Image 1 (cartoon, each protein chain N blue to C red):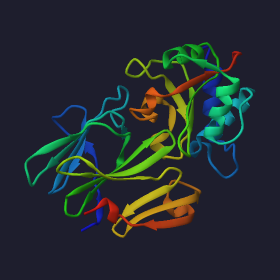
Image 2 (tube, rainbow over the protein chains, first blue to last red):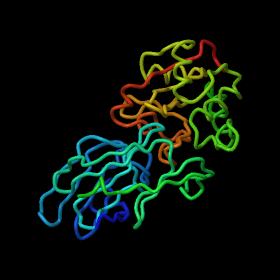
Image 3 (cartoon, rainbow over the protein chains, first blue to last red):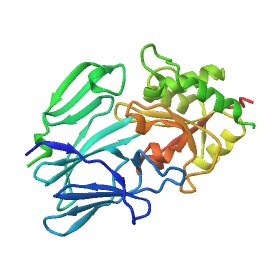
Length: 148
Length: 146
């Protein structure tokens, strides 16, 4: 249950300029403050809203980003939310506690193409395209440190 | 338009590869180097960090993103840059409306992904995050490109 599943982030009808997504465990939401884009690929402005569906409670992630819209992942047990955040050319993968919204783990991935699937994390270098599979070097890194 | 030359430089440099086999859209320094090439503007050599050291030494430092957009609107080449521990980042400031009344519109390639990339529809404030966008440096070349 240390598996991570991508969580699609989509417009919420009734909540103007909100994008989010959910599963049985956690809901996740961003506000889109880009004036010229109704279909943004990322979220520079916090907070990020995290709703723990078990507890009924929710909390805010007050600083961070820029969060990638395609980059949100939920742990199987619902206790962790893994996010891709980037600034400039740098990037990282950050795992937050879904109850507290506290950073549990953080890993600098700058320069590497990347992917998250059932098996774990993959990072790669020397690439033709954004697909990690175009990489002449591919390392499998464990997601264990993001879990627990 | 007065800043048009630079807009064109950016557009063209988008699909080039300044370093062979690495598309500009995936490499910030490469995209900048290409823009400087087309406009015939001397540019420091190497990766992002190195280019920032270069601009720091040999280029004029502007006071703010707003002032940077002023220069860029005058047809000057203006580079916004900030160094990272390893991968720094640089972008071409273009004229236009400031974002959150602060951050100017830019063109940049990025190895971070499509998200870090700007075809002129993002400002430095949507490329660098909440903390970095306040630490940016803006460099201008002493002579207009138009």
